[PDB]
Length: 103
Length: 103
Image (cartoon, rainbow over all chains, first blue to last red; front, side):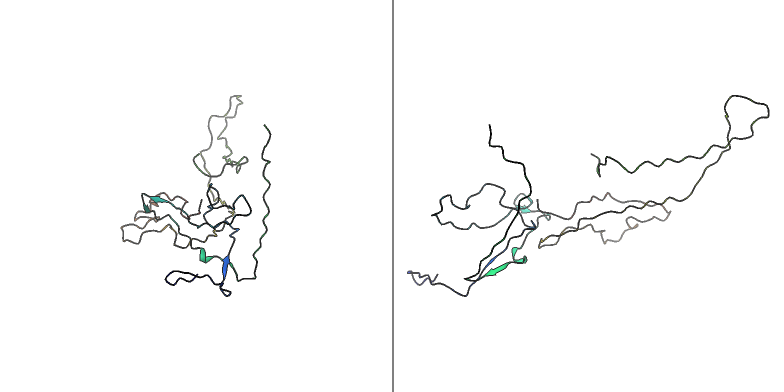
């Protein structure tokens, strides 16, 4: 996006890249456990914004205890994708008891 | 509750005893059991060897951990070492939890 005293114009950038990684070793704070917004919308016609990623650690008051560990995500291997690349991964669930829908 | 590994079949107990040796039984026969023995004790080495299995530490935390470090300040007696009279002393209890995993 280019802004010049208003009238900003969007022009596709072919060369730039988008980098994606799935941890799969569970070495990151797991944010997904709690209910939050920004999931895929219910109704497929919608278009959704991808939510930001942050995390909390141990603390005393507002100050940080030496225990708190700060993770840098840049430090994992991640696949980089220009226009015309696709990133696909497959996951298999461990066996878990049925959910009981009966009353 | 104290700590450690609850086992259903613990390492079996090893019990040891000196076989009693009678001392100078009288010539004429008497049914009452011996009240007097040789006074003796035994001694020797004992060797215990345990093979521990470990869980290697694999993490991505950026900043440095906390470690167990003996302080570098000069003192009368080094910690975990004999004193001038030969009495070995443990200065402080050492818990096992230092490395940090995210919850």
